[PDB]
Image (spheres, coloured by chain):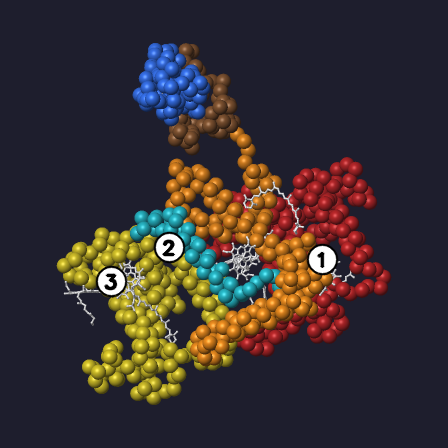
Amino acid sequence: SHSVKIYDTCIGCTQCVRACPTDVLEMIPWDGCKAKQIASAPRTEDCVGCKRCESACPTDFLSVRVYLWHETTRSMGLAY
Amino acid sequence: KPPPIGPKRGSKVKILRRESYWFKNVGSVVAVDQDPKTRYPVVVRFAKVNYANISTNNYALDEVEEVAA
Amino acid sequence: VAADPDRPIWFPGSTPPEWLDGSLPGDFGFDPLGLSSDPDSLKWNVQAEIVHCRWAMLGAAGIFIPEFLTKIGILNTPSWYTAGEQEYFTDKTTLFVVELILIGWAEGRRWADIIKPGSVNTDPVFPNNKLTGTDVGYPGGLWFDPLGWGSGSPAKLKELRTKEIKNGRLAMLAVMGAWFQHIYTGTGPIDNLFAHLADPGHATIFAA
Amino acid sequence: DISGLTPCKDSKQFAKREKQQIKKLESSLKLYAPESAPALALNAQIEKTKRRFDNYGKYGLLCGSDGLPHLIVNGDQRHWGEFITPGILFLYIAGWIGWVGRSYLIAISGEKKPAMKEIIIDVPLASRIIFRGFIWPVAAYREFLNGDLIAKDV
Amino acid sequence: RATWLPGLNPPPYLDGNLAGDYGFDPLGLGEDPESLKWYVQAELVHSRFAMLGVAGILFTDLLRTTGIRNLPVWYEAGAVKFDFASTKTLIVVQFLLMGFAETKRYMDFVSPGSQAKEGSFFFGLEAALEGLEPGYPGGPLLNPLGLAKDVQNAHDWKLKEIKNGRLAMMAMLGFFVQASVTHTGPIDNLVEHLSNPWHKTIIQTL
Amino acid sequence: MRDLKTYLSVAPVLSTLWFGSLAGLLIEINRLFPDALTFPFFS
Ligand code: CLA
Ligand code: CLA
Ligand SMILES: CC(/C=C/C=C(C)/C=C/[C@@]12O[C@]1(C)C[C@@H](O)CC2(C)C)=C\C=C\C=C(C)\C=C\C=C(C)\C=C\[C@@]12O[C@]1(C)C[C@@H](O)CC2(C)C
Ligand SMILES: CC1=C(/C=C/C(C)=C/C=C/C(C)=C\C=C\C=C(C)\C=C\C=C(C)\C=C\C2=C(C)CCCC2(C)C)C(C)(C)CCC1
Ligand code: SF4
Ligand code: SF4
């Protein structure tokens, strides 16, 4: 559904996923920062698009980035 | 090199990054990650915050340029 | 400017404020609102009190002495309230401008003396002249202090300066009393005094 | 007499506006005694109206067919009191406002937290600057020549 | 020194070595140094023109009021139709000549060596325009007497100049306003003040 | 007090002081000089 992307300007603060209410994100090891971790987005099918991840990305503009795309029943957040 | 690679701690620096909030704005280098594998070591501290209420950001060496002052 | 921690205060039993150490000439600790909590605000309000006191003393004299030596020590003075309506050898707006130009000179020298403590002591025309005043608000010069009484021990000077502002405070009160009297009452101040001394009961502010 | 407009000192409908407003204020004047506060205030407003109309007559205002003063902005020397002299009077004050504000923001720019000086206005600083905009048409011109008016990008 | 009001330090961007300083710049106009230089030359020229103005008004009105010559009032003096020449010609001639004067002064201010070096022909006089100083040109054309040959060590002369000129400028503003609300000459207003000073001032104009 | 003057210098208190003074100025001008459409001095 939605296309979440994490760019290399990350600082590995783990606020994107700790804010993400649908388990879309997960921190993985990395070698590009002092924290040695970066966020990944495997479960984009569960992505609703609420952008709580990028409302908590403390960078110049953003590192995590949500692109609104094909909306399915779970990206639209429907219990019916 | 083990000696510093980037600007000095406190050197007021300009941002050449086009996507940053402080583009063509001065800054204040507070640290430079001397590890020769990180991509954006230059930790800058600006005076005015961005839209996310943040005054600091990491920048590269080529995405930065010190002023004549 | 020596402190007196156990001086008599305006309101005995009260604790006077910290910014009134007793140093000033006549500080009985009366500052409830805190209008002199700051040091510079206190230094300004001191000179404000001093000059309001001195102007009010000259005012009280020029009101009551022309009103005392008119009702009994017979002379001819129009009034103190309606003296601004009377006419003289100059237009009313003209001599106002003249006394403004002449008083603003001295008041600008005072402004300089307050901002810079010693700046205006040399006579700009005759620099050999001088005012030997170290204390702000008390210029020890010939034109102000020719008789040499504004010098000496700081304790005698302090008791003399509190004598000054003590006379001046009730001079202020007396002048605004004459104001409110000539407004509420029709006649002049000394006539009000005689009407009070005739019948202290049925002569007061109350008329109903 | 330009733009087909007759002057107000020799206009008929302007005097008619005068007479109509005066009769309107007099109709509201025959309901009180001629010495009380309402009648005195109405007579004062009447004299205000009459002097207003006569002043608009004597200044050479141009009153159209509707009988109201039509201001000329083109730049006619007779009608610089309409726009150009008060326009300069405006721009002098407006640039005063802008220049004292700009010099204030530049004054606090070298502060640790300048924004608190925009909330808590440093009245001594501004008051020392508040008269510095009296000379704005020359100080700003020099700041433009010296290069201090417009900032540089870096 | 004595800087124009005691109790205030002079601004640090002007002090001492300048023609009659006294430290009066409360509105920060001489804060920038080149601005101060331009304003110094402006002041000198303004004060000299104003001094010539006060002389040409006071002298003419001494001749007029006393009755030595039937010269016109300073207020109504521009519309005198001269027989040999017209004002329409005089404005153009003034434009030409004072342009050759003031543009030369300017090009010296921006480049002091100019007007004397090369191809600066003024009837072969390319030496009297040496300048020697900003605001104080010198030379046989401009100071024939040469009271102040030196100009840096002539602080007394330049101080006298600038003080008399500040006072002449203030007197010219006096002539401007005093004779726009009273519509007489300065000498008339003076003898009106020297008859009854306490009854003829600015504020005695109702 | 220093803090009372710090509060009096705050933007709304100083704004209402400034605009009350200004409004009194313009008000008294439009009472002393009412009904004004043209600047007649040197007109
Ligand atoms: C002209 C007014 C004036 C001013 C500026 C001062 C200033 C000062 N006095 Mg003085 N004083 C005055 C009049 C004044 N006094 C009078 C008239 C009295 C007798 C009633 C006193 C009695 C007095 C005592 C006993 C003491 C002082 C002290 C002081 C100092 C500290 C208090 C302060 O910050 O005052 C600042 C005062 C003002 C800014 C004036 C207040 C203005 C508000 C608007 C007043 C409004 C209410 C008022 C009651 C209405 C007046 C009506 C009137 C007709 C009765 C300061 C130097 C103390 C000190 O250190 O002594 C040296 C001290 O111990 N004063
Ligand atoms: C932007 C559009 C606009 C415009 C252009 C106007 C224009 C005007 N209105 Mg209207 N008005 C408007 C919007 C507008 N109004 C709105 C929105 C309302 C509803 C709130 C009103 C309600 C209204 C009423 C109810 C009245 C007006 C009036 C006026 C007149 C005011 C003249 C006056 O008293 O100024 C005189 C000048 C001043 C008050 C400014 C003085 C500035 C000080 C003195 C500083 C300047 C001196 C300084 C020291 C510099 C000098 C030079 C030197 C020292 C350098 C003028 C024609 C009045 C009028 O007479 O109508 C014709 C009137 O009765 N208006
Ligand atoms: C009353 C007065 C001041 C009163 C102040 C008080 C009570 C202050 C109280 C407080 O601040 C303190 C102390 C401490 C704070 O913590 C608390 C409060 C409570 C806030 C001043 C009068 C001040 C009065 C003055 C300065 C009077 C001057 C008079 C003159 C010059 C008269 C001249 C003439 O009378 C002649 C000579 C002849 C006539 O014909 C013409 C004229 C012109 C009328
Ligand atoms: C005459 C007239 C007219 C017209 C006019 C015109 C057309 C004009 C134009 C003009 C123009 C075309 C202009 C332009 C400009 C530009 C620019 C570019 C500018 C800039 C400026 C600046 C920058 C400034 C600033 C400042 C100041 C000085 C003030 C305050 C402060 C500040 C800082 C803001 C008419 C007829 C209608 C009417 C009458 C009048
Ligand atoms: S991209 Fe943002 S949320 Fe994700 S690890 Fe980096 S700083 Fe944390
Ligand atoms: S948009 Fe919402 S659901 Fe999608 S990754 Fe961001 S926080 Fe998670």
Helix, strand or loop for disc 3? loop
Instruction: Determine which residue is flagged by label 3.
Output: C26
Of the pair E170 and C125, the residue shown nearer to us: E170
Instruction: Determine which residue is flagged by label 2.
Output: C117
Kind of residue indicated by mark 3? Gly
Residue at 61% across / 61% down in the picture?
F38
Q: Colour of chain F?
A: cyan
Respond whether the residues carrying marks 2 and 3 are from the same subunit.
Answer: yes
**In this view, D130 is above or below D113:** below
Q: Colour of chain E?
A: red
Chain given the colour yellow: C
Q: Is residue A80 among the parts visible in the rendering?
A: yes
Instruction: Determine which residue is flagged by label 1.
Output: D3
Q: Is mark 3 within 8 Å of ligand 1?
A: yes
Dot 2 alpha-carbon crowd within 10 angstroms: few under 14, some 14 to 19, many 20 or more: some
Where is residue C143? Give x, y as percent: 39, 68
Report the quarter where the N terminus of chain C lies: bottom left
Q: Extreme left residue here?
A: C13
Q: Is residue B11 among the parts visible in the rendering?
A: no
Q: Colour of chain B?
A: brown
- In the image, which is nearer the foreground, mark 2 or mark 1? 1
Q: Extreme front residue here?
A: A80
Report ligand 3 position as a quadrant. Answer: bottom left
CB within 8 Å, label 2 to label 1: no
Helix, strand or loop for disc 1? helix
Kind of residue indicated by mark 2? Pro
Residue at 44% across / 24% down in the picture?
A61
